[PDB]
Amino acid sequence: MQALLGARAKESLDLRAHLKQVKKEDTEKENREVGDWRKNIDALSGMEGRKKKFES
Amino acid sequence: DEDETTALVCDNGSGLVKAGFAGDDAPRAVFPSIVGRPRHQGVMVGMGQKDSYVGDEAQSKRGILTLKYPIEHGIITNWDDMEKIWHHTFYNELRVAPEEHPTLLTEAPLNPKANREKMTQIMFETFNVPAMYVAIQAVLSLYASGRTTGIVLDSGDGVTHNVPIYEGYALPHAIMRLDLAGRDLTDY
Image (cartoon, rainbow over all chains, first blue to last red):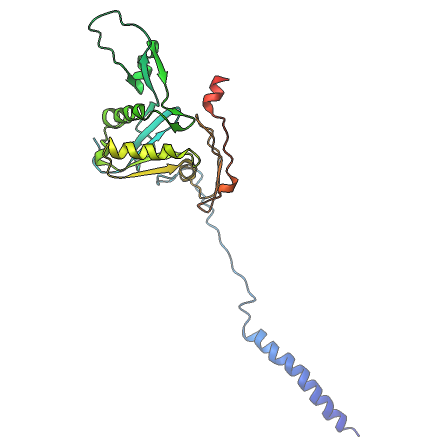
């Protein structure tokens, strides 16, 4: 009386935690696309002089 | 007098003509867009005296001259006076003979077609320029200002064209041409 419902619970937890597991696999093996970037700036710090080109 | 066959640039406004060579940061000389003519009877013999004076000559001798502008609200109507101004500008003072140099002229995008057509004809037929290019003031202003994008509101002497450009593209449906310019401000 104690073994059958145990086995059924094992199967159900297996299927659910296993879909959870296969998707969490994709989450963990690649966590790079969920990252970000520094996005630096040059900002042209030279407001003391101008440029050589004809347009400037 | 130049040591390179660079292009020439001549900005012929309804006010003054700014001219020099391509690649510089300034016109080499500025001439008024004027041909002057005496409005008096000569009294003395052997005085020289021209039938017409050109550019800075017209202003220098202006005490007895009526001074006319060949260009009205940005458009050339008196091509003969334009040719006189250009010959003086290019050969006497800027020292660049167009025959040896390609030439760029300037105009509003809605300047009537005769302007760009007549200017092109004169530089090729009376000056024998090897090449020509009539440029638009809105393009020229954004290049001078270091922009690709912006509104060019040219509050010049002739006509104001008010032309928007974005990422180098014209946005012609948004052009507001206004018949108000520096010459009218002077008249007021």
